[PDB]
Image (cartoon, helix red, strand yellow):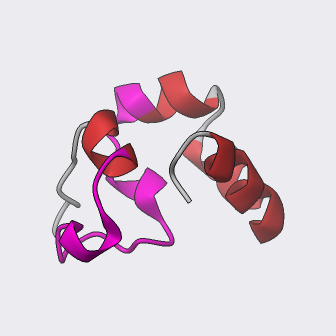
């Protein structure tokens, strides 16, 4: 599929739900971070993060303003 559009970390964290770009799945904001931002925010690979239980992915994101 087409490579996902990336958005700055500050935009994904600080945008009202109603104003979120239509192409962003609000439950998977991490997928729209650049690889650099994902690494800075989570400190692990995308696949390692995806292997954590869903509730743990969400809980980590909540504190980080991404869920």
Instruction: Name the residue at 50% across, 72% down.
Output: 27
Q: Residue at x 63, y 25 (%)?
A: 43
Residue 3 position by quadrant: bottom left
Q: Is residue 18 left or right of residue 62?
A: left
- Say which quadrant the C terminus sits in: bottom right
In the shown orientation, is residue 65 left or right of residue 22?
Answer: right
Residue 58 lies, in percent from the top left, at 69, 60
Q: Position of residue 42 (x, y in %)?
A: 61, 33
Residue 2: which quarter of the image? bottom left
Q: Residue at x 25, y 76 (%)?
A: 18
Can I make out residue 24 in this image? Answer: yes
Q: Is residue 50 magenta?
A: no
Q: How many dots with numbers?
A: 0
Residue 32 vs residue 27: left or right?
left
Q: Is residue 14 above or below residue 37?
A: below
Residue 53 visible (yes or no): no
Task: Look at the image and say whether residue 25 sits in the magenta stretch.
Answer: yes
For this view, does 38 lie left or right of residue 9? right
* Residue at 23% in and 61% down: 4
Magenta residues (range): 14-37
Q: Position of residue 8 (x, y in %)?
A: 24, 37
| Quarter of the image where the N terminus is located | bottom left
């Amino acid at each position: 599929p087409t490579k996902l559009e990336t958005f700055p970390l500050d935009v994904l964290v600080n945008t009202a739900a109603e104003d979120l770009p239509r192409g962003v799945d609000p439950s998977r904001k991490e997928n729209y971070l650049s690889d650099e931002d994902f690494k800075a925010v989570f400190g692990m690979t995308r696949s390692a993060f995806a292997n954590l239980p869903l509730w743990k992915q969400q809980n980590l994101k909540k504190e980080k303003g991404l869920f």
